[PDB]
Amino acid sequence: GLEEKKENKQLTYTTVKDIGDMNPHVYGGSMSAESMIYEPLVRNTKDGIKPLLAKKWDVSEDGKTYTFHLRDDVKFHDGTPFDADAVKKNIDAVQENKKLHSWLKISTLIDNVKVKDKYTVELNLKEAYQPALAELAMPRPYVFVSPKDFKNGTTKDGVKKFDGTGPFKLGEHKKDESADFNKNDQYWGEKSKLNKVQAKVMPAGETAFLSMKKGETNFAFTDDRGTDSLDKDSLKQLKDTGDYQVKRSQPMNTKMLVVNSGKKDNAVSDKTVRQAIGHMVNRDKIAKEILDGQEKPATQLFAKNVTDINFDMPTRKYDLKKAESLLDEAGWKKGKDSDVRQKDGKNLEMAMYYDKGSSSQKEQAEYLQAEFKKMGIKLNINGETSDKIAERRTSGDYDLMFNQTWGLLYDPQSTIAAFKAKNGYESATSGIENKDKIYNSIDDAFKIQNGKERSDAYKNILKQIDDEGIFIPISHGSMTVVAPKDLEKVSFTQSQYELPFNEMQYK
Ligand SMILES: C[C@H](N[C@@H](CCN[C@H](Cc1c[nH]cn1)C(=O)O)C(=O)O)C(=O)O
Ligand SMILES: [Cl-]
Ligand SMILES: [Zn+2]
Protein backbone atom coordinates (compact mmCIF):
# COMPACT_ATOMS: atom_id res chain seq x y z
CA GLY A 1 0.00 0.00 0.00
CA LEU A 2 0.84 3.65 0.04
CA GLU A 3 2.28 3.63 3.53
CA GLU A 4 4.63 0.76 2.87
CA LYS A 5 5.91 2.41 -0.32
CA LYS A 6 6.54 5.58 1.71
CA GLU A 7 8.31 3.54 4.39
CA ASN A 8 10.44 1.71 1.83
CA LYS A 9 11.19 4.80 -0.21
CA GLN A 10 9.59 3.48 -3.32
CA LEU A 11 7.62 4.87 -6.15
CA THR A 12 5.69 2.71 -8.51
CA TYR A 13 4.17 4.39 -11.45
CA THR A 14 1.39 3.19 -13.68
CA THR A 15 1.89 3.40 -17.45
CA VAL A 16 0.29 1.87 -20.44
CA LYS A 17 3.55 1.02 -22.15
CA ASP A 18 6.80 -0.85 -21.45
CA ILE A 19 10.20 0.93 -21.40
CA GLY A 20 11.13 -0.52 -24.84
CA ASP A 21 14.74 -0.47 -26.15
CA MET A 22 16.82 1.38 -23.58
CA ASN A 23 19.62 2.13 -25.99
CA PRO A 24 19.54 5.92 -26.01
CA HIS A 25 21.41 6.20 -29.28
CA VAL A 26 18.07 5.34 -30.96
CA TYR A 27 14.59 6.60 -30.23
CA GLY A 28 12.32 3.69 -29.38
CA GLY A 29 12.84 3.71 -25.58
CA SER A 30 10.91 5.47 -22.90
CA MET A 31 12.30 9.02 -22.66
CA SER A 32 11.83 9.49 -18.98
CA ALA A 33 13.34 6.13 -18.21
CA GLU A 34 16.44 6.95 -20.22
CA SER A 35 16.81 10.34 -18.49
CA MET A 36 16.96 8.46 -15.15
CA ILE A 37 19.94 6.41 -16.26
CA TYR A 38 21.87 8.27 -18.96
CA GLU A 39 23.27 11.85 -18.95
CA PRO A 40 24.45 14.43 -21.47
CA LEU A 41 27.59 16.53 -21.22
CA VAL A 42 25.48 19.59 -20.31
CA ARG A 43 21.91 20.39 -19.31
CA ASN A 44 19.61 22.90 -20.94
CA THR A 45 17.69 24.60 -18.08
CA LYS A 46 15.38 27.61 -17.77
CA ASP A 47 18.55 29.49 -16.74
CA GLY A 48 20.45 28.40 -19.88
CA ILE A 49 23.11 25.74 -20.31
CA LYS A 50 24.56 24.26 -17.14
CA PRO A 51 27.42 21.81 -16.39
CA LEU A 52 26.74 18.14 -15.98
CA LEU A 53 29.19 15.47 -17.14
CA ALA A 54 31.31 18.38 -18.46
CA LYS A 55 32.27 20.84 -15.69
CA LYS A 56 33.41 23.54 -18.11
CA TRP A 57 34.02 24.07 -21.77
CA ASP A 58 35.75 26.42 -24.18
CA VAL A 59 34.53 27.45 -27.61
CA SER A 60 37.19 28.46 -30.15
CA GLU A 61 37.18 31.96 -31.73
CA ASP A 62 35.80 30.66 -35.08
CA GLY A 63 33.09 28.69 -33.15
CA LYS A 64 34.14 25.26 -34.66
CA THR A 65 35.89 23.66 -31.73
CA TYR A 66 34.30 22.91 -28.34
CA THR A 67 36.69 21.64 -25.65
CA PHE A 68 34.95 19.98 -22.70
CA HIS A 69 36.62 19.56 -19.32
CA LEU A 70 35.05 16.47 -17.90
CA ARG A 71 34.27 15.52 -14.32
CA ASP A 72 36.88 12.99 -13.02
CA ASP A 73 34.71 11.26 -10.46
CA VAL A 74 32.13 9.62 -12.72
CA LYS A 75 31.68 5.89 -13.20
CA PHE A 76 29.29 3.97 -15.42
CA HIS A 77 26.90 1.58 -13.71
CA ASP A 78 29.15 -1.39 -14.58
CA GLY A 79 32.09 0.26 -12.74
CA THR A 80 34.02 1.31 -15.86
CA PRO A 81 35.17 4.98 -15.83
CA PHE A 82 33.70 7.92 -17.60
CA ASP A 83 36.40 9.89 -19.36
CA ALA A 84 37.33 11.49 -22.67
CA ASP A 85 37.67 8.11 -24.33
CA ALA A 86 34.11 7.15 -23.41
CA VAL A 87 32.82 10.45 -24.72
CA LYS A 88 34.62 10.03 -28.05
CA LYS A 89 33.47 6.47 -28.53
CA ASN A 90 29.79 7.40 -27.74
CA ILE A 91 29.81 10.30 -30.15
CA ASP A 92 31.62 8.37 -32.88
CA ALA A 93 29.06 5.52 -32.42
CA VAL A 94 26.16 7.91 -32.80
CA GLN A 95 27.76 9.54 -35.85
CA GLU A 96 28.29 6.17 -37.54
CA ASN A 97 24.49 6.20 -37.77
CA LYS A 98 23.96 9.88 -38.48
CA LYS A 99 21.12 9.38 -41.04
CA LEU A 100 18.80 8.61 -38.04
CA HIS A 101 19.87 11.88 -36.42
CA SER A 102 19.54 14.32 -39.25
CA TRP A 103 16.55 15.90 -37.58
CA LEU A 104 19.16 17.45 -35.28
CA LYS A 105 21.44 19.71 -37.22
CA ILE A 106 24.54 19.25 -35.15
CA SER A 107 24.73 15.59 -36.33
CA THR A 108 25.27 17.06 -39.86
CA LEU A 109 28.05 19.38 -38.62
CA ILE A 110 30.14 17.07 -36.47
CA ASP A 111 33.49 16.52 -38.19
CA ASN A 112 35.44 14.57 -35.55
CA VAL A 113 36.10 14.10 -31.90
CA LYS A 114 39.60 14.16 -30.35
CA VAL A 115 40.82 13.16 -26.92
CA LYS A 116 43.28 15.78 -25.57
CA ASP A 117 43.97 14.16 -22.18
CA LYS A 118 42.13 11.78 -19.83
CA TYR A 119 39.34 14.29 -18.99
CA THR A 120 39.54 16.65 -21.97
CA VAL A 121 37.68 16.03 -25.21
CA GLU A 122 37.50 18.25 -28.27
CA LEU A 123 34.50 18.28 -30.60
CA ASN A 124 35.26 19.72 -34.02
CA LEU A 125 32.45 21.08 -36.20
CA LYS A 126 32.39 21.82 -39.96
CA GLU A 127 31.05 25.30 -39.11
CA ALA A 128 30.15 27.41 -36.12
CA TYR A 129 26.74 26.60 -34.68
CA GLN A 130 25.32 28.27 -31.62
CA PRO A 131 22.62 25.67 -30.79
CA ALA A 132 25.40 23.04 -30.45
CA LEU A 133 25.33 23.02 -26.65
CA ALA A 134 21.55 22.94 -26.63
CA GLU A 135 21.47 19.89 -28.95
CA LEU A 136 24.15 18.15 -26.89
CA ALA A 137 21.81 18.65 -23.83
CA MET A 138 19.05 16.56 -25.39
CA PRO A 139 18.05 13.21 -23.85
CA ARG A 140 18.87 11.44 -27.09
CA PRO A 141 21.15 10.80 -28.84
CA TYR A 142 24.24 12.34 -27.32
CA VAL A 143 24.18 10.70 -23.86
CA PHE A 144 26.71 8.26 -22.59
CA VAL A 145 26.50 4.41 -22.59
CA SER A 146 29.40 2.34 -21.10
CA PRO A 147 31.72 1.50 -24.03
CA LYS A 148 31.98 -2.07 -22.62
CA ASP A 149 28.30 -2.41 -23.61
CA PHE A 150 28.90 -1.63 -27.25
CA LYS A 151 28.69 -4.45 -29.82
CA ASN A 152 32.10 -4.56 -31.53
CA GLY A 153 32.47 -0.89 -30.93
CA THR A 154 28.95 0.06 -32.24
CA THR A 155 25.56 1.02 -30.79
CA LYS A 156 23.54 1.46 -33.99
CA ASP A 157 22.42 -2.22 -33.81
CA GLY A 158 22.00 -2.24 -30.03
CA VAL A 159 23.99 -2.50 -26.89
CA LYS A 160 24.66 -5.53 -24.69
CA LYS A 161 23.57 -3.92 -21.38
CA PHE A 162 22.13 -0.51 -20.43
CA ASP A 163 24.84 1.10 -18.21
CA GLY A 164 24.71 4.93 -17.98
CA THR A 165 26.11 7.34 -15.49
CA GLY A 166 22.80 8.58 -14.07
CA PRO A 167 21.28 8.57 -10.58
CA PHE A 168 19.40 5.35 -11.31
CA LYS A 169 20.39 1.97 -12.72
CA LEU A 170 18.17 -0.33 -14.77
CA GLY A 171 17.30 -3.47 -12.81
CA GLU A 172 14.77 -6.23 -13.21
CA HIS A 173 12.62 -5.81 -16.27
CA LYS A 174 9.74 -8.20 -16.99
CA LYS A 175 8.50 -7.46 -20.45
CA ASP A 176 5.10 -5.67 -20.52
CA GLU A 177 4.86 -5.93 -16.76
CA SER A 178 7.47 -3.97 -14.79
CA ALA A 179 10.90 -2.28 -14.93
CA ASP A 180 12.96 -1.36 -11.88
CA PHE A 181 15.09 1.77 -11.67
CA ASN A 182 17.29 1.28 -8.59
CA LYS A 183 19.17 4.03 -6.73
CA ASN A 184 22.73 4.40 -7.92
CA ASP A 185 24.68 4.49 -4.69
CA GLN A 186 27.85 5.43 -6.62
CA TYR A 187 26.17 8.31 -8.37
CA TRP A 188 28.48 11.29 -8.69
CA GLY A 189 25.93 14.10 -8.26
CA GLU A 190 22.70 14.54 -6.23
CA LYS A 191 21.95 10.98 -5.13
CA SER A 192 18.40 9.73 -5.20
CA LYS A 193 16.42 9.79 -1.91
CA LEU A 194 14.18 7.06 -3.38
CA ASN A 195 15.51 3.48 -3.28
CA LYS A 196 13.56 2.43 -6.29
CA VAL A 197 11.22 3.70 -8.97
CA GLN A 198 9.27 1.05 -10.77
CA ALA A 199 7.46 1.39 -14.08
CA LYS A 200 4.42 -0.87 -13.91
CA VAL A 201 2.63 -1.58 -17.17
CA MET A 202 -1.21 -1.81 -17.18
CA PRO A 203 -4.14 -0.63 -19.24
CA ALA A 204 -5.35 2.86 -18.76
CA GLY A 205 -8.86 3.66 -17.36
CA GLU A 206 -10.41 1.56 -14.59
CA THR A 207 -7.39 -0.73 -14.15
CA ALA A 208 -4.96 2.12 -13.64
CA PHE A 209 -7.43 3.90 -11.32
CA LEU A 210 -7.99 0.91 -9.04
CA SER A 211 -4.23 0.10 -9.03
CA MET A 212 -3.63 3.62 -7.76
CA LYS A 213 -6.55 3.73 -5.21
CA LYS A 214 -5.22 0.63 -3.48
CA GLY A 215 -1.52 1.80 -3.63
CA GLU A 216 -0.25 -0.97 -5.92
CA THR A 217 0.93 1.98 -7.96
CA ASN A 218 1.32 5.39 -6.36
CA PHE A 219 2.45 7.68 -9.06
CA ALA A 220 1.52 8.69 -12.65
CA PHE A 221 2.62 11.08 -15.23
CA THR A 222 1.99 11.98 -18.88
CA ASP A 223 4.10 9.56 -20.91
CA ASP A 224 6.39 10.56 -23.78
CA ARG A 225 3.59 10.21 -26.33
CA GLY A 226 1.32 12.47 -24.24
CA THR A 227 -0.90 9.85 -22.80
CA ASP A 228 -2.32 10.22 -19.24
CA SER A 229 -3.50 6.94 -17.80
CA LEU A 230 -6.10 8.68 -15.61
CA ASP A 231 -9.02 10.84 -16.65
CA LYS A 232 -10.30 14.03 -14.85
CA ASP A 233 -12.73 12.11 -12.64
CA SER A 234 -10.05 9.58 -11.58
CA LEU A 235 -7.87 12.47 -10.61
CA LYS A 236 -10.81 13.84 -8.54
CA GLN A 237 -11.39 10.54 -6.87
CA LEU A 238 -7.67 10.19 -6.00
CA LYS A 239 -7.36 13.73 -4.53
CA ASP A 240 -10.54 12.92 -2.61
CA THR A 241 -9.00 9.90 -0.91
CA GLY A 242 -6.77 12.31 1.03
CA ASP A 243 -3.68 10.25 -0.15
CA TYR A 244 -2.83 11.93 -3.48
CA GLN A 245 -1.91 15.40 -4.87
CA VAL A 246 -2.01 16.43 -8.59
CA LYS A 247 0.47 18.84 -10.21
CA ARG A 248 0.21 20.20 -13.76
CA SER A 249 3.04 21.89 -15.60
CA GLN A 250 2.82 25.06 -17.57
CA PRO A 251 1.40 24.37 -21.13
CA MET A 252 4.11 22.63 -23.11
CA ASN A 253 2.89 21.63 -26.56
CA THR A 254 0.20 21.82 -29.19
CA LYS A 255 -1.93 18.67 -29.62
CA MET A 256 -3.04 18.32 -33.23
CA LEU A 257 -4.56 16.25 -35.96
CA VAL A 258 -2.06 15.18 -38.61
CA VAL A 259 -3.53 14.89 -42.15
CA ASN A 260 -1.55 12.74 -44.54
CA SER A 261 -0.98 14.63 -47.80
CA GLY A 262 1.08 11.68 -48.91
CA LYS A 263 -1.70 9.07 -48.71
CA LYS A 264 -2.35 8.82 -52.48
CA ASP A 265 -5.04 6.09 -52.27
CA ASN A 266 -7.33 8.41 -50.13
CA ALA A 267 -9.18 11.72 -50.32
CA VAL A 268 -6.90 13.32 -47.68
CA SER A 269 -4.26 13.56 -50.50
CA ASP A 270 -6.51 16.27 -52.11
CA LYS A 271 -5.67 19.70 -50.71
CA THR A 272 -9.32 20.72 -51.01
CA VAL A 273 -10.55 17.88 -48.84
CA ARG A 274 -7.83 18.71 -46.31
CA GLN A 275 -9.07 22.33 -46.23
CA ALA A 276 -12.61 21.10 -45.74
CA ILE A 277 -11.61 18.85 -42.83
CA GLY A 278 -9.95 21.89 -41.29
CA HIS A 279 -13.30 23.59 -40.86
CA MET A 280 -14.81 20.44 -39.31
CA VAL A 281 -12.95 20.51 -35.96
CA ASN A 282 -14.71 22.37 -33.23
CA ARG A 283 -11.65 23.04 -31.09
CA ASP A 284 -13.52 25.45 -28.77
CA LYS A 285 -16.12 22.96 -27.80
CA ILE A 286 -13.57 20.09 -27.64
CA ALA A 287 -11.50 22.19 -25.19
CA LYS A 288 -14.40 23.27 -23.07
CA GLU A 289 -16.56 20.17 -23.09
CA ILE A 290 -14.49 17.10 -24.04
CA LEU A 291 -11.26 18.14 -22.21
CA ASP A 292 -13.21 19.74 -19.34
CA GLY A 293 -11.52 23.08 -19.69
CA GLN A 294 -8.18 21.54 -18.64
CA GLU A 295 -6.48 22.66 -21.85
CA LYS A 296 -6.92 25.78 -23.84
CA PRO A 297 -7.78 25.52 -27.47
CA ALA A 298 -4.99 25.96 -30.04
CA THR A 299 -5.52 28.11 -33.14
CA GLN A 300 -2.05 27.64 -34.54
CA LEU A 301 0.59 24.89 -34.45
CA PHE A 302 3.07 26.80 -32.30
CA ALA A 303 1.60 29.33 -29.91
CA LYS A 304 2.47 33.02 -30.26
CA ASN A 305 4.51 32.82 -27.00
CA VAL A 306 6.82 30.03 -28.35
CA THR A 307 10.42 31.19 -29.03
CA ASP A 308 10.83 32.75 -32.47
CA ILE A 309 7.13 32.61 -33.27
CA ASN A 310 5.65 35.80 -31.80
CA PHE A 311 2.91 36.03 -34.45
CA ASP A 312 -0.79 35.29 -34.67
CA MET A 313 -1.62 33.04 -37.62
CA PRO A 314 -5.13 31.73 -36.72
CA THR A 315 -5.93 28.61 -38.67
CA ARG A 316 -9.24 27.58 -40.35
CA LYS A 317 -12.24 28.01 -38.02
CA TYR A 318 -15.03 25.65 -37.28
CA ASP A 319 -17.47 26.28 -40.12
CA LEU A 320 -19.50 23.49 -41.63
CA LYS A 321 -20.91 25.53 -44.58
CA LYS A 322 -17.39 26.30 -45.55
CA ALA A 323 -16.62 22.53 -45.27
CA GLU A 324 -19.63 21.61 -47.37
CA SER A 325 -18.73 24.10 -50.02
CA LEU A 326 -15.08 22.83 -50.19
CA LEU A 327 -16.17 19.18 -50.34
CA ASP A 328 -18.56 20.08 -53.18
CA GLU A 329 -15.68 21.82 -55.03
CA ALA A 330 -13.67 18.63 -54.66
CA GLY A 331 -16.54 16.70 -56.28
CA TRP A 332 -17.43 14.84 -53.07
CA LYS A 333 -21.13 15.67 -53.28
CA LYS A 334 -24.03 14.12 -51.35
CA GLY A 335 -27.27 13.30 -53.25
CA LYS A 336 -31.05 13.78 -52.84
CA ASP A 337 -31.08 10.02 -52.18
CA SER A 338 -28.78 10.42 -49.14
CA ASP A 339 -26.68 12.75 -46.99
CA VAL A 340 -23.55 10.57 -47.74
CA ARG A 341 -20.72 11.92 -49.91
CA GLN A 342 -19.51 10.17 -53.05
CA LYS A 343 -17.21 10.64 -56.00
CA ASP A 344 -16.64 8.26 -58.94
CA GLY A 345 -18.98 5.71 -57.37
CA LYS A 346 -16.99 5.50 -54.05
CA ASN A 347 -18.06 6.72 -50.61
CA LEU A 348 -15.91 9.27 -48.78
CA GLU A 349 -14.07 7.45 -45.96
CA MET A 350 -10.95 7.95 -43.96
CA ALA A 351 -9.13 6.07 -41.30
CA MET A 352 -8.20 7.96 -38.13
CA TYR A 353 -5.75 6.53 -35.53
CA TYR A 354 -5.48 7.44 -31.88
CA ASP A 355 -3.68 6.06 -28.82
CA LYS A 356 -6.12 3.58 -27.13
CA GLY A 357 -4.41 4.39 -23.91
CA SER A 358 -5.66 8.07 -24.12
CA SER A 359 -9.25 8.55 -22.99
CA SER A 360 -9.06 12.13 -24.19
CA GLN A 361 -7.84 11.05 -27.67
CA LYS A 362 -10.58 8.40 -27.78
CA GLU A 363 -13.37 10.80 -26.78
CA GLN A 364 -12.12 13.25 -29.42
CA ALA A 365 -12.03 10.53 -32.04
CA GLU A 366 -15.66 9.58 -31.16
CA TYR A 367 -16.83 13.14 -31.33
CA LEU A 368 -15.23 13.80 -34.64
CA GLN A 369 -16.52 10.56 -36.05
CA ALA A 370 -20.08 11.73 -35.15
CA GLU A 371 -19.34 15.20 -36.55
CA PHE A 372 -17.94 13.69 -39.82
CA LYS A 373 -21.01 11.47 -40.23
CA LYS A 374 -23.21 14.61 -40.26
CA MET A 375 -21.14 15.75 -43.21
CA GLY A 376 -21.53 12.43 -45.02
CA ILE A 377 -18.01 11.13 -44.33
CA LYS A 378 -17.43 7.77 -42.84
CA LEU A 379 -14.58 8.22 -40.33
CA ASN A 380 -13.26 4.83 -39.23
CA ILE A 381 -11.49 5.23 -35.89
CA ASN A 382 -8.81 2.85 -34.65
CA GLY A 383 -7.36 2.88 -31.13
CA GLU A 384 -3.86 1.42 -31.14
CA THR A 385 -0.70 1.51 -29.02
CA SER A 386 1.34 4.66 -29.23
CA ASP A 387 4.14 2.43 -30.61
CA LYS A 388 1.87 1.49 -33.53
CA ILE A 389 0.80 5.16 -34.02
CA ALA A 390 4.51 6.06 -34.28
CA GLU A 391 5.22 3.35 -36.80
CA ARG A 392 2.30 4.59 -38.87
CA ARG A 393 3.70 8.15 -38.57
CA THR A 394 6.95 6.89 -40.10
CA SER A 395 5.45 4.60 -42.77
CA GLY A 396 2.59 6.86 -43.89
CA ASP A 397 -0.04 4.23 -43.39
CA TYR A 398 -2.79 6.50 -42.09
CA ASP A 399 -5.24 9.16 -43.27
CA LEU A 400 -5.53 11.11 -39.98
CA MET A 401 -3.92 10.64 -36.61
CA PHE A 402 -3.73 12.36 -33.26
CA ASN A 403 -0.30 13.65 -32.39
CA GLN A 404 1.48 16.47 -30.54
CA THR A 405 4.42 18.77 -30.85
CA TRP A 406 7.59 18.05 -28.94
CA GLY A 407 7.64 20.76 -26.24
CA LEU A 408 9.64 23.70 -24.96
CA LEU A 409 13.17 22.54 -25.97
CA TYR A 410 12.07 21.34 -29.44
CA ASP A 411 9.32 23.73 -30.57
CA PRO A 412 9.63 25.28 -33.04
CA GLN A 413 12.99 24.60 -34.60
CA SER A 414 13.22 20.76 -34.05
CA THR A 415 9.56 20.08 -34.70
CA ILE A 416 9.83 22.05 -37.94
CA ALA A 417 13.01 20.16 -38.94
CA ALA A 418 10.87 17.02 -38.31
CA PHE A 419 8.48 18.10 -41.07
CA LYS A 420 11.06 16.57 -43.43
CA ALA A 421 12.33 13.80 -41.24
CA LYS A 422 11.34 10.16 -41.78
CA ASN A 423 10.98 9.67 -38.02
CA GLY A 424 8.86 12.82 -37.69
CA TYR A 425 6.15 14.11 -39.97
CA GLU A 426 7.70 13.70 -43.46
CA SER A 427 4.92 11.25 -44.30
CA ALA A 428 2.29 14.03 -43.79
CA THR A 429 4.17 16.68 -45.75
CA SER A 430 5.33 14.40 -48.52
CA GLY A 431 2.30 15.07 -50.75
CA ILE A 432 2.71 18.91 -50.87
CA GLU A 433 3.46 20.02 -54.42
CA ASN A 434 5.92 22.76 -53.36
CA LYS A 435 7.66 20.45 -50.95
CA ASP A 436 11.13 20.96 -52.49
CA LYS A 437 10.91 24.80 -51.87
CA ILE A 438 9.44 24.42 -48.34
CA TYR A 439 12.08 21.83 -47.25
CA ASN A 440 14.83 24.11 -48.59
CA SER A 441 13.28 27.04 -46.78
CA ILE A 442 13.36 24.96 -43.59
CA ASP A 443 17.11 24.38 -44.01
CA ASP A 444 17.70 28.04 -44.79
CA ALA A 445 15.68 29.24 -41.79
CA PHE A 446 18.01 27.56 -39.34
CA LYS A 447 21.01 29.50 -40.70
CA ILE A 448 19.40 32.97 -40.08
CA GLN A 449 21.08 34.74 -37.12
CA ASN A 450 18.73 37.67 -36.74
CA GLY A 451 15.72 36.77 -34.55
CA LYS A 452 13.21 38.75 -36.47
CA GLU A 453 14.35 37.51 -39.91
CA ARG A 454 14.23 33.94 -38.57
CA SER A 455 10.76 34.34 -37.12
CA ASP A 456 9.70 35.60 -40.53
CA ALA A 457 11.28 32.66 -42.29
CA TYR A 458 9.33 30.37 -39.91
CA LYS A 459 6.18 32.34 -40.63
CA ASN A 460 6.59 31.92 -44.35
CA ILE A 461 7.02 28.11 -43.83
CA LEU A 462 4.12 27.76 -41.44
CA LYS A 463 1.79 29.84 -43.59
CA GLN A 464 2.32 27.40 -46.47
CA ILE A 465 1.99 24.42 -44.19
CA ASP A 466 -1.27 25.91 -42.81
CA ASP A 467 -2.46 26.49 -46.40
CA GLU A 468 -1.95 22.80 -46.99
CA GLY A 469 -4.06 21.65 -44.05
CA ILE A 470 -1.40 19.14 -42.89
CA PHE A 471 -1.88 19.89 -39.18
CA ILE A 472 -5.10 20.81 -37.39
CA PRO A 473 -4.29 22.29 -33.97
CA ILE A 474 -6.73 21.45 -31.21
CA SER A 475 -5.53 22.12 -27.65
CA HIS A 476 -2.34 22.92 -25.61
CA GLY A 477 -1.07 20.09 -23.57
CA SER A 478 0.57 20.11 -20.16
CA MET A 479 2.41 17.48 -18.22
CA THR A 480 0.30 16.11 -15.39
CA VAL A 481 1.63 14.22 -12.39
CA VAL A 482 -0.24 12.31 -9.67
CA ALA A 483 1.92 11.74 -6.58
CA PRO A 484 1.52 10.72 -2.87
CA LYS A 485 0.46 13.75 -0.84
CA ASP A 486 3.63 13.46 1.23
CA LEU A 487 6.07 13.27 -1.72
CA GLU A 488 8.01 16.54 -1.78
CA LYS A 489 10.06 18.00 -4.57
CA VAL A 490 7.99 16.95 -7.52
CA SER A 491 8.67 19.62 -10.07
CA PHE A 492 9.00 20.16 -13.86
CA THR A 493 12.01 20.89 -16.09
CA GLN A 494 11.75 22.45 -19.57
CA SER A 495 10.96 18.98 -20.94
CA GLN A 496 7.72 17.03 -21.14
CA TYR A 497 9.88 13.86 -21.24
CA GLU A 498 11.59 13.70 -17.80
CA LEU A 499 11.05 14.22 -14.14
CA PRO A 500 13.49 14.78 -11.22
CA PHE A 501 13.14 11.40 -9.71
CA ASN A 502 16.43 11.77 -7.83
CA GLU A 503 15.19 14.93 -6.07
CA MET A 504 11.84 13.62 -4.90
CA GLN A 505 11.57 12.77 -1.23
CA TYR A 506 8.95 11.65 1.26
CA LYS A 507 7.44 13.73 4.14
C1 LIG B 1 14.18 11.79 -33.01
C2 LIG B 1 12.60 11.82 -32.95
N1 LIG B 1 12.03 12.54 -31.82
C3 LIG B 1 12.80 13.05 -30.58
C4 LIG B 1 12.04 14.04 -29.73
C5 LIG B 1 10.53 13.92 -29.91
N2 LIG B 1 9.95 12.82 -29.15
C6 LIG B 1 8.50 12.60 -29.38
C7 LIG B 1 7.99 11.61 -28.37
C8 LIG B 1 8.63 10.29 -28.58
C9 LIG B 1 8.37 9.31 -27.79
N3 LIG B 1 9.10 8.28 -28.18
C10 LIG B 1 9.80 8.63 -29.23
N4 LIG B 1 9.53 9.90 -29.49
C11 LIG B 1 8.01 12.36 -30.84
O1 LIG B 1 8.83 11.90 -31.74
O2 LIG B 1 6.79 12.75 -31.05
C12 LIG B 1 13.25 11.94 -29.63
O3 LIG B 1 12.56 10.93 -29.65
O4 LIG B 1 14.27 12.11 -28.89
C13 LIG B 1 12.06 10.41 -32.98
O5 LIG B 1 11.16 10.05 -32.19
O6 LIG B 1 12.64 9.67 -33.78
CL1 LIG C 1 -2.73 29.00 -30.20
ZN1 LIG D 1 10.62 11.18 -30.69
Image (cartoon, grey):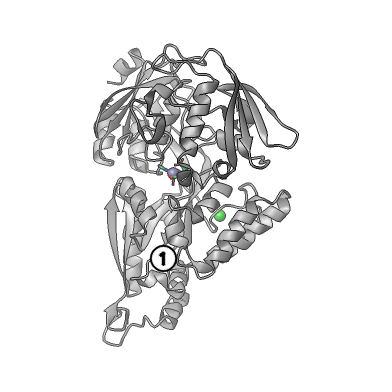
Q: Residue at x 37, y 29 (%)?
A: 152
Image spot of residue 422 (x, y percent) = 44, 53
Establish if 69 lies above or below 346.
Answer: above
Q: Secondary structure at mark 1?
A: loop
Left/right placement of residue 371 relative to residue 250 reads left
Quarter of the rendered structure image containing ligand 3: top left
- Residue sitting at the far bottom: 336
Q: Is residue 38 above or below residue 316?
A: above
Q: Which residue is tagged 1?
A: 262
Residue at the image position 45 percent from the left and 80 percent from the top: 325
Residue 371 in view, yes or no = yes
**Crowd class of label 1 (few under 14; some 14 to 19; many from 20; radius 10 Å):** many
Amino acid under disc 1: Gly
In percent of the image, x 50 and y 33: which residue is there? Answer: 92
Judging depth in this view, the residue of 256 and 141 nearest the camera is: 141
- Pick the front one: 58 or 401: 58
437 sits left or right of 386 in the view:
right
**Is residue 362 shown to the viewer in this render?**
no
